[PDB]
Length: 142
Length: 426
Image (cartoon, rainbow over all chains, first blue to last red; front, side, top):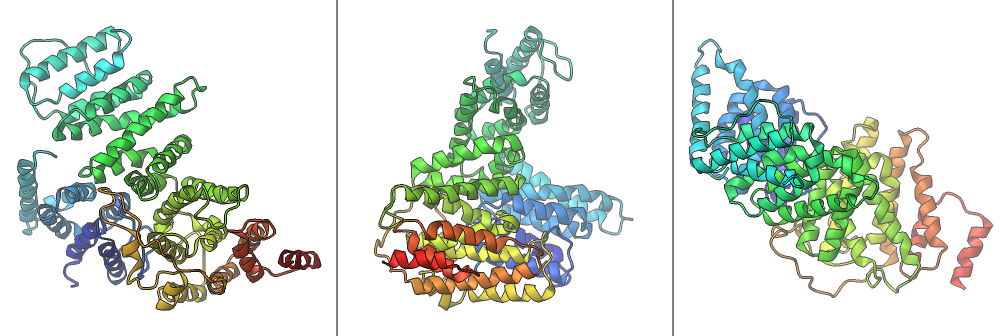
């Protein structure tokens, strides 16, 4: 589990915007564990709880967390985007609109990895770019 | 033609993103005539021509023109928006996404017309806001984007909250308690309250305290039978949604939030009683994770233990939602945007004033723990004043509950007060 902090972070954010009230609460608890275990620096404070009522409208709250971790936690970028794009194709139309909202703040971090001494990381950004090209071709309504 | 520059401009921009190359060229030329006739100040230069080849991908070009005219041509705002929304409903899905892109910059200009000397212009901005509410209800696939674009920005405009909030309540009132229009407007305010947490909360609480205070004019045997029950039921769903993530600003409103809870514990349909339990859980959770307050490490342990007690089966009984596995499931419904829930099981349990003591004495402990680390706190004095005002006034639906609370949180009593209590018994 300590080798994939970026993979679990996408599962937490994606399911915070769900339409099932129980599914939101468990997603909030998962996000609290990471911020403690991995010492991730977020803006506010979080506390695990049972019985929370989390509103269905959660777009702006999710983006604030995503927009903050991206600014001051760049080393999750490659794991996050590879998983964020993968979850894009497995979700419904309404959730497809959400992933675009909190995905964009991370695209700006690909600069740090574009010329990373050809350490096979440069070979991965080219893989990420290929995924974005596939989405553009298929989704004609958005 | 000189009386409707705003209406012609929307036809130009909307058709500039068509999928037909011939239609795109006609749109470019029409946009050039407007800029010449009306001397509109755009960034670049334009020139009419025949035979231009215009790419189908044109979003960023269209938005730049709209984003500029909005900044330095405000006098088109009321004509443009009225026509932009109207053509929004006549277009296909793909074009609908474009209308949101270049519509957003024009919303900031409504400040200049909100208080325009009641010249019937104030009557139009309220008309426009009604149209936006109608769009939000119908288009459910674009919902995550409308919140972050339309309602997200309007929250940050301080001068416009009062009018925007006012229209929200009226729309919900017509629908009714379980209506769709009321459920959306309750869930939509969360986006609105993000920009100004303090101003939106004080207004929603301000209105809830006054409606209860106005039940004294026409007393009724119970609160539900009153004529203002609907106005108090929908406004409770607004507070439920704003409680999460400390959007009610507990740091300055705690005395009143406890005050409303006591008058609402265990009253109404099972879906409303599950909301009052959830509201308390969210308020306590907000105290623990609030930064404006500096609680000692000892006190935080007191709150965290209380946060667990309220979820025990003992307290599900006090709030009247026994036989319920989880309150969160009952409070919310997945199909709120689709249909309107039909209330059932009109049979409702009776409430005993001995249960109101146990709840009213668990909350008092919570408040006192917080007052130790807050110098010169006035939470308890403010709460006591509200209790007095309702204890010694005739209202068959509220007076019994105010008396039970008044003797529980009061720290002093004089002969005169003890005289009035006996007189009430007489």
